[PDB]
Length: 107
Length: 241
DNA sequence: TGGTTTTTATATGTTTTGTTATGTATTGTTTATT
DNA sequence: AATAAACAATACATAACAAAACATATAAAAACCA
Image 1 (cartoon, rainbow over the protein chains, first blue to last red):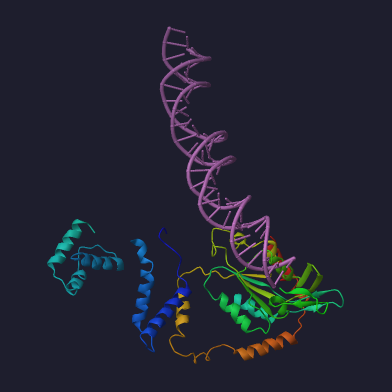
Image 2: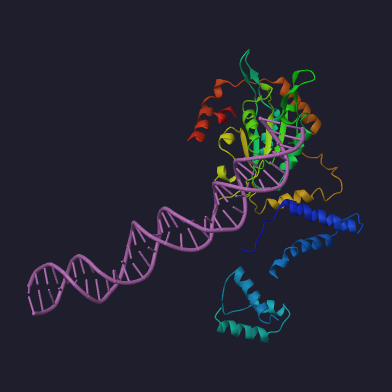
């Protein structure tokens, strides 16, 4: 698109490997750790980044949508959603309010 | 296709001649085009490390006055009147020096007509040229004959072209990055021997034995499948290639 | 005459086609050297 | 004859637009039955 430029090449992957080797050479180590690659990728992404210059019931909604993406049944008998809400960490009053809100929203 | 072509390009073929006025050499001139940043230069160096004669780029007759004689003084293709010759950046090359490669495409000769010398001479090896799609690096919305900015007369006479375009996607480039880091997994590739791979010293001995011990004849029995293979591109340089 | 239909004048919209200006890329021209 | 390099002159791709072909609409004229 509009702000795009170039594409990913294997020479850039080789340069990322070379920059990780240079970062390991600057730390005088015989091995390449995980700290060099995450610095090199941050370096190559911030090299182009200068051009731009709660969940209280949303978690319950994602849990209900995960159960709606595996089977897709909007029933009135909830026996598994109440068990995963009990093992998810929160209470049942917010669960009942979320059930009433999404039944009012008709999902 | 590319590795098979350079393998049979260094295998050569059959060079047969007549008694007085005819000669033919089993030879293929190859060209590479498509997406950049892949193994192209690697190949362009690897083959320079395989052949015993070749330059990484024609010669010229001279009337030497000290001995009053027509000497020749050269390098490049002239030196490699045997083996291969590697040329990179074919599209950025000038048009004045394209006329000498226009003769070495299928004629394998040098015809100099200048001050002091009018001489045609022997100059056959095979070219290996790597080119680029102008500024395009290949476009799917344009034809192949216009995307590389290469003349049709000089490209129909080319024996073999190679679309070495990448067309990046999944479950391919992932194996590419995995194979490039698999030798970075260990500090030394001592584990390169337990696979189906011939060594270099056995390969060059087999290639040198096959190039100097086999003179194959093209019988009439393969006539019928050749005619129909020609008409599919027709619906003589391709037939000679 | 009198209503009704048909053509024309006026008015605007749509798509194809051809012209021109211009910034950038290509190509020719000259001179020194091999 | 070829190469190189600095410079000038020309061509080219496209932007912006004009204009003609192609197309429709409706109030006023104009035939025209009747």
